[PDB]
Image (spheres, rainbow, N blue to C red):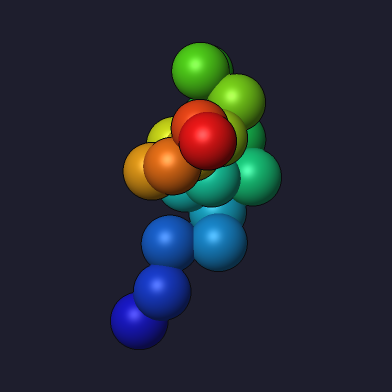
Length: 20
């Protein structure tokens, strides 16, 4: 039960746990 729909229709684009 992933969240492909959540990230697909997100508001802030992606989470990006790591920036660098």
